[PDB]
Image (cartoon, rainbow, N blue to C red; front, side, top):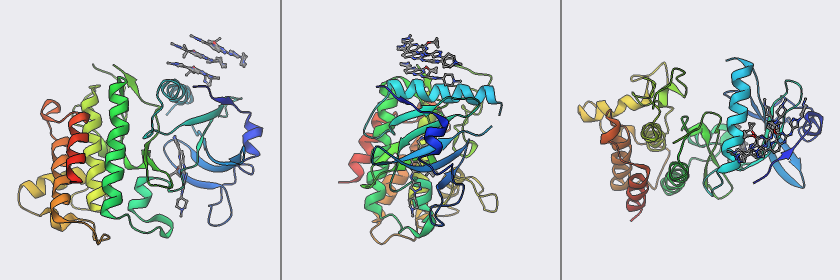
Length: 288
Ligand SMILES: CN1CCC(n2cc(Nc3nc(OC4(C)CC4)c4nc(-c5cnn(C)c5)ccc4n3)cn2)CC1
Ligand SMILES: CN1CCC(n2cc(Nc3nc(OC4(C)CC4)c4nc(-c5cnn(C)c5)ccc4n3)cn2)CC1
Ligand SMILES: CN1CCC(n2cc(Nc3nc(OC4(C)CC4)c4nc(-c5cnn(C)c5)ccc4n3)cn2)CC1
Ligand SMILES: CN1CCC(n2cc(Nc3nc(OC4(C)CC4)c4nc(-c5cnn(C)c5)ccc4n3)cn2)CC1
């Protein structure tokens, strides 16, 4: 697959000079990370998302921009975001993607901008879709290294689409430890590079789908959502205590079936964790 080489001013045109005001206000800014700002645009009579990279050295940022392109050139799947083009220019790095009508999983779980809560049926399909996207990357010998709800984007049909490949690796140890701390496997925080870590991170994403809570809340007991696993095992709290109350269609059997998959993904021992193929098989058996 080949990408369109855009000019910074030819991208400044579609985003109305990268209007930093929100969409609701009438601007073009639709969100931010980690590591730049996602902007709304229209080009070839189609809506696009333009991410403007912000500088955590600028030489290391350029490497992630390059990794992104390399992975996006090789990998293409139904449950993966598609790269449209990029702007190289003089210290101005921008990536172009197709606009995701429903934004991110993080934002739909928090009902940001007054969006309706996701039903348990929509949540099961989003989890299945995301596991299919991770399956494609693991089959194509890639490790994402940053599986999180802000990187699981959603289209008009709520089709889960994995994004941000700026840290992905082919198929081990490393001195430069990267990823999101609230989602990292114990061994990943220790410098190991294994697709078994991507499973741990997906286990956190699943607890977010069950609870509607963020992975980390400094003003919460426990601060890390992955710790609720221990509270449940210790009978300190139940799964019912943690189930998102913003659902009317969540049956106790399939919620506990999804919790079982998350609990297994969240094993301390990377080898005692199921592979993405077992994850997909369990998530499929959950909608039966
Ligand atoms: C600082 N940086 C700014 C941006 C700059 N730049 C890149 C392009 N275009 C481009 N670059 C590719 O190489 C990489 C990813 C940059 C290293 C590339 N690679 C593949 C490919 C196919 N299979 N695989 C495994 C990879 C396909 C298409 C590609 N197109 C234009 N400007 C590079 C330097
Ligand atoms: C200042 N800077 C401006 C921009 C300029 N620049 C141009 C490119 N274009 C590019 N580069 C590739 O390089 C590698 C090998 C991926 C890294 C590349 N590779 C493949 C390919 C297909 N199979 N494999 C194994 C690789 C296809 C197309 C490609 N296009 C990248 N940077 C550099 C200097
Ligand atoms: C300031 N600067 C602006 C940009 C301008 N510039 C344009 C290019 N375009 C380019 N460069 C490639 O490769 C090199 C030179 C980076 C390594 C390249 N490679 C492949 C390819 C296909 N298979 N493989 C394995 C590689 C395809 C297309 C490519 N296009 C390079 N510099 C120079 C001056
Ligand atoms: C009420 N409504 C307000 C509007 C709302 N909404 C829709 C979008 N569309 C969107 N947003 C992206 O980014 C986020 C979620 C803002 C941060 C995004 N990102 C990429 C991407 C792929 N890789 N990388 C590195 C980035 C591709 C496509 C995208 N599409 C944003 N908000 C829906 C609900």
